[PDB]
Image 1 (tube, rainbow over the protein chains, first blue to last red):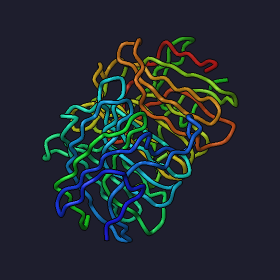
Image 2: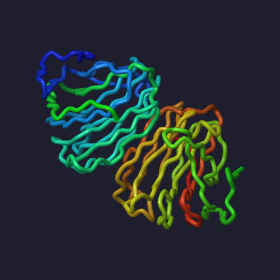
Image 3: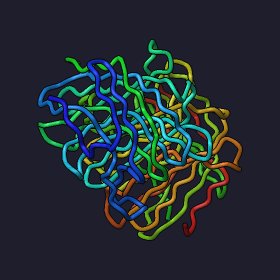
Length: 179
Length: 179
């Protein structure tokens, strides 16, 4: 059954729609460079011990620095992966952070509509393939690595407000299935 | 003193210019997904045990699938990092691969001129910050992680031809210095 990691004050959970409103100063980051350990981001999903392909359509109102919305894959508090859009110096970026004791993040240009995009995560064997889409048809690769956690993987939708509060993210067309 | 990792058949080494012509089927990759271990890419540089900032201007004639040219940071054969342009399905991408026993790669859109760009690597403490530039003035972030190797880091220019032979890459404006 679906459950939360840092359940937010405000939210909505329907059969085919999930809304996460971030709490103040929420984020996910481990040590690397910044020297702090944040594990306060919001994630709604479920644990699974089998391979899978997760896909979701994200609609959030990015505005404050470091606003994040996308997907999350958890193992432990020091073994997880997050990916999606992140606001910074205006322009929106698409990136990913793989944390295996330490956070390793990559980022880059996001061409689509920052307020309406798709995310896809495929986890078969010990491999993690993360892709995104701006039209729901084309899925460019974002990150390809090997899972840093164990058997149990927590897969779900995520939302972060490192410098603010209230980022509202709507998740629809959610589909968790065999790879 | 400067030395090679998989010295190529053809090359040129001047005081302020380095040309690497790739040998057939050369590449850098460790296990993840593809299930093969490649350590045949060409790298010209030097070992250092102190923090540094490396910068270089790259001019290569990308054409065959997976053609790569950029920078490399080595620790061991299972602990290294590479970053730069990579040709694929025509369009050129800017990406990075961090290998800590297993390769973890990120990729994305490259807006500049694929045949003339800059790379910058900063290694202070145990942090690695990789940036690129399309005009030699602006340096967007590409990857930020913590070094997977030890004290001795091999920093230098790199060139790969996974599916061909002959990719000629020219490296100029090389500058290795304190961060």
